[PDB]
Length: 51
Length: 226
Image (cartoon, rainbow over all chains, first blue to last red; front, side, top):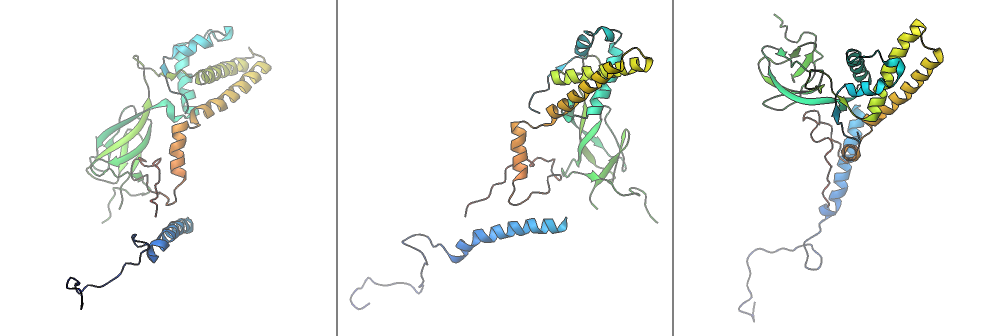
């Protein structure tokens, strides 16, 4: 940068999709419990279909 | 069962029967037979002694223990995998899968040629004398007393030495105490209801506790929080 000799970084650029300095609560995180419940209930459904 | 099976010797029942003047010709010899008959007719699994005993299979056949009455499980010794009932009609017969078993007498017919199998079986608790040993549960004792009284009165009625009303009363009382004794030994305790509860509520059903020795049947099913 022009005025600050100490401003430098690496080629790596990115972002965390977080809320207020926390770890990111992703979309998959907030859909995962429902997917697990779906899998368990469909397990019951399949075992019912077998019997 | 809520209560504990404290063992007592067989003539405890003759203490109680012989209170009746009409049962004074009863003996230990008669009590043994009718006690074994009562034990079988009720079919309570808490009255038997659980034992585990390994045997060798020579070729689809193995020698069975002497005191065996009923088998809880058979499994392979090296793997621990349980065996199922054999449905095959030509098991070791060749022409020109998973392991299973079949037991008739002193012989167990497995589908495996040469392995050691572990058998978890039920026997009768014996006395210092080679005799059956009965629970001291006064419900069990009263029901066995009423069983023997009912049989003796049935003989005496076949003779005509007892009134039909007396036999009818004896049969009524024995029937009620038989039902009550059945419920006493079978209704689970608190720990057995925790095991049954942990068997009952599974979000992910567990359907393979036969493979193990039903070890994890009453284990609680934990779901991680997300």
